Length: 105
Length: 105
Image (cartoon, rainbow over all chains, first blue to last red):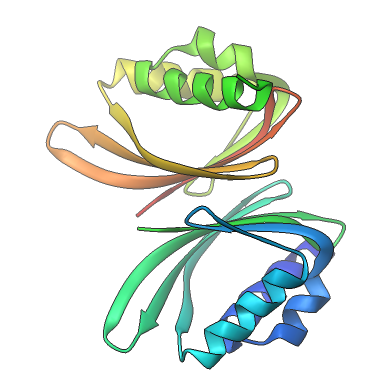
């Protein structure tokens, strides 16, 4: 399995399990994440994952695509009968994620 | 207006107007684009834009977000009463687009 696929898999697993220690394996101190325009940098990203789990938010992968270093995922996000889809784009370089955007659909 | 914003604007305008000559201003010969997993490279990307216009497909921007070099757009895509949303992710570096993914929602 190529390094880029391992990193994408771990990112998804970190979101699906709300696992900050998995998130730490794939990000770097200058990773940027935008969630509907709210910006998180570095360790803020890890803390945002911890809040997924604390809030009981359930994330599941629907589908994905890839073009070079860019990946795009469709996920469902559920919080007690509230449910939406999000598009999550990532840039993976050498097994680490530099940039993440999540947008609600 | 920063170069990254000019490039994003032109990409959207190329899609909204189905204008291959605008697309040529923002891509490079090794630009990769995936449309639901169908891969286009370089001039194939330009030809794909020409087909938008030939087919009478109407694309409109709904919203967008940005994180560093990564942009994510939500667009509507309409073909005679058939309508869907697509998420379109791009990586912009120095005013040119390297990678594009479009996924139907």
